[PDB]
Length: 105
Length: 6
Length: 176
Length: 50
Ligand SMILES: *[C@@H]1O[C@H](CO)[C@@H](O[C@@H]2O[C@H](CO)[C@@H](O)[C@H](O)[C@H]2NC(C)=O)[C@H](O)[C@H]1NC(C)=O
Ligand SMILES: *[C@@H]1O[C@H](CO)[C@@H](O[C@@H]2O[C@H](CO)[C@@H](O)[C@H](O)[C@H]2NC(C)=O)[C@H](O)[C@H]1NC(C)=O
Ligand SMILES: *[C@@H]1O[C@H](CO)[C@@H](O)[C@H](O)[C@H]1NC(C)=O
Ligand SMILES: *[C@@H]1O[C@H](CO)[C@@H](O)[C@H](O)[C@H]1NC(C)=O
Ligand SMILES: *[C@@H]1O[C@H](CO)[C@@H](O)[C@H](O)[C@H]1NC(C)=O
Ligand SMILES: *[C@@H]1O[C@H](CO)[C@@H](O)[C@H](O)[C@H]1NC(C)=O
Image 1 (cartoon, each protein chain N blue to C red):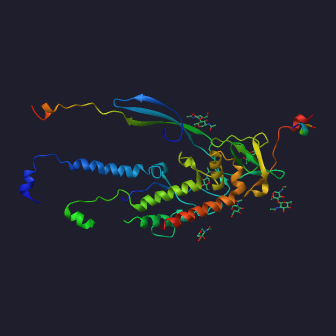
Image 2: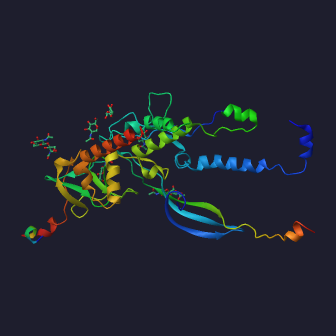
């Protein structure tokens, strides 16, 4: 609506019978080609992303923001559980990290 | 969480 | 053809010039209406050869790929469900001017959009089209309407059934 | 010539494959709208009559 692509803001500029809008919009540009898992299966618990999408370069799975590649390690802190793995169409087995364990000293 | 910490 | 009339008429503006401005108006509307279907995909996306769309058998809304008419089956119904003397109108002095774009061209764009949407994340509207599995694409939509995205996958077969059935009921209903 | 509808291609769909962007660029772009005609008026007893 406000220009093309994901709108940030606009400015008015006057014109002799009208207005010019400058639209500032985000456009994503370079990209990659990867596999996405619909969900991750852990120890029977399915896990789902709290915000993003699961992605992988093949060595390991990573959860990333939808609109700019910035991986982080999949963990309890960034995924939520929802029942067993068996219900999902094509779930993939992995660990889920959990931050707690180094604190158990 | 406390059950986890035990 | 009356000469004498054509002399007596030499007294006024050629007001059908202004009509023609409406006509090109209509043509740019016919573009504009579907510039999202047209201009916002300068890429003419083809449907993939793959059909593993998560069990969502939406085949009938795609272009009928085998047919010369590249319309969907449902589009073919719609085209027929509209009840579509012109040669007399012409010789009487009133003239249709053809569409700027044929229905084949138009339906090719409509196909392009069906294809873009199903094949790709909505960033194709932002031009940077990205492939995405259709299931994932719907799961985000559910999260967009505040349903937690686990719920789709937990019921994906049921949704796919319901969807297919609803499309069914539509094209049944479009028989009348 | 018969015009080309655009650039033909296909998105590499598959039931497992995602693409995600990396570098981005800020588009700035102009949109334009009219806001008024010129105000005019006509005394009939100047236009219709001298
Ligand atoms: C990865 O996931 C698959 C599918 O969930 C697991 O396959 C199952 O493995 C158990 C244990 O051997 C079998 O009893 C099931 O019959 C298997 N199911 C299928 C669909 O083959 C596999 O074991 C998982 N791998 C790990 C390390 O958990
Ligand atoms: C995103 O793209 C811009 C544009 O190429 C990159 O900026 C370039 O960076 C290199 C190395 O520092 C310079 O030699 C070029 O002159 C820069 N170009 C411009 C116009 O800025 C930027 O580095 C990229 N960033 C990432 C991480 O993708
Ligand atoms: C993504 O995959 C498609 C299909 O092979 C390929 O044509 C395209 O070049 C790939 N692009 C990149 C940059 O990975
Ligand atoms: C994938 O990412 C991991 C994490 O940084 C890295 O160790 C690995 O080398 C990467 N491999 C490829 C092929 O990109
Ligand atoms: C994707 O399709 C391939 C080929 O049919 C199939 O082997 C694979 O299991 C599919 N994966 C899922 C879970 O969609
Ligand atoms: C889709 O539904 C139609 C109508 O029943 C059927 O003929 C066709 O085989 C179906 N195809 C698939 C793969 O679902």
